[PDB]
Length: 346
Ligand SMILES: CC(C)=CCC/C(C)=C/CC/C(C)=C/CC/C(C)=C\CC/C(C)=C/CC/C(C)=C/CC/C(C)=C/CC/C(C)=C/CC/C(C)=C\CC/C(C)=C/CC[C@@H](C)CCOP(=O)(O)O[C@@H]1O[C@H](CO)[C@@H](O)[C@H](O)[C@@H]1O
Ligand SMILES: Nc1nc2c(ncn2[C@@H]2O[C@H](COP(=O)(O)OP(=O)(O)O)[C@@H](O)[C@H]2O)c(=O)[nH]1
Image (cartoon, rainbow, N blue to C red; front, side):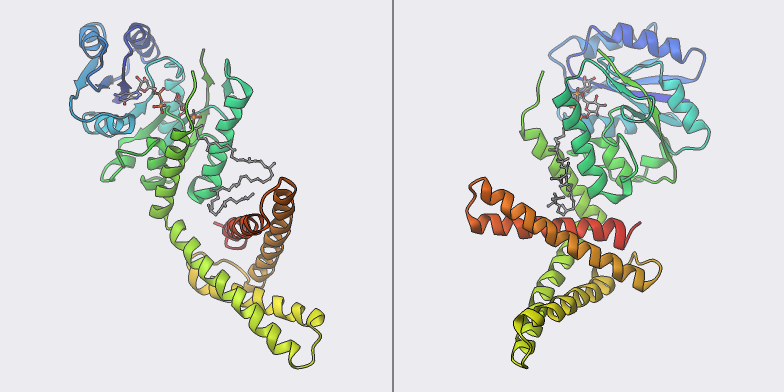
């Protein structure tokens, strides 16, 4: 039995077409429609209860708690199906792909994502710059949350999941996107993605911080924020050991220009040690030597980046200290990422 969770705000002119084509695609099968409307200044909450004659439609309206992810959480609570399908009422999400979503869940996947960006997937009547802010955020997600590194459209509002995935789980009401909360905090072993087409208005830069604020939150939960802190404490530890050996070498008659080289190299080694027994102690794999060599490529990558970022900022007219500092900060940035996805890959 399938519950099709449709959260709404000001959506009257679609419920007809919506329910018609939901029912059309699911003809015969055991399904319901749980609608969660947050007291719409629109007839929606009433028109749905109206349409509950032709179509299997439950309608909960709430007067005290609103928000999309807030709804879907309740949409889970108030459902009664073996499989949840979540989508949007506007019809940007086609009810006809819903049968693919469940079939996929039938053949053993825990979560079936309706995906813009798998082979088969399409986006139309979207401009290039709105099309690629998308792939760019998605790209911040996949890199920053290694759990979902391999998911093409992990920010979809259109997905199906077994009821088990999200039960006994405190999903977060605020979270900007609920499918994300689920991929991070839910219980599962398999995820597929189904190709669909995004069907036939702007959004300020404030929600961009809201999306990023979500990702920072997922990160604290996942422990990455914790790792990054410790990684930084080593980084400082290395910045110290680099200098301490330099002084120790110039004073023993090693010309600074020769001296710097063992200095930096013992500094890369020091860094490797403490990261491999503190920050990424959990996720070590294979040869320690192969991990060591990996770390070197990451150090080097961090340095090449510091350099390039510094000069490009300078040439843009940025103050040398800001430019030097932004150089260091994006250097720890890239060094971490590579270490996280290559040196200690998972
Ligand atoms: C360069 C280096 C990597 C800097 C390090 C970065 C930092 C410092 C890392 C520090 C360590 C930590 C943070 C680890 C994590 C790292 C991570 C966070 C970032 C690292 C990745 C790096 C920085 C990327 C770059 C490194 C570069 C400089 C290198 C030069 C080479 C290359 C060529 C350079 C390219 C430049 C690069 C690619 C820029 C990446 C960002 C761009 C600018 C796009 C930001 C966009 C986001 C933020 C907008 C908000 C999202 C909206 C869009 C929501 C809305 O989403 P949707 O609408 O789609 O969602 C839908 O919603 C609708 C509702 O209608 C539903 O119907 C749908 O189903 C669906 O749900
Ligand atoms: N109940 C409820 N539904 C919402 C809310 N926000 C959006 N919706 C519904 O979500 C679907 C698409 O949401 P949309 O606003 O386009 O995406 P968003 O930008 O991530 O919030 C539509 O069917 C809306 O009716 C909300 O706060 N409460």
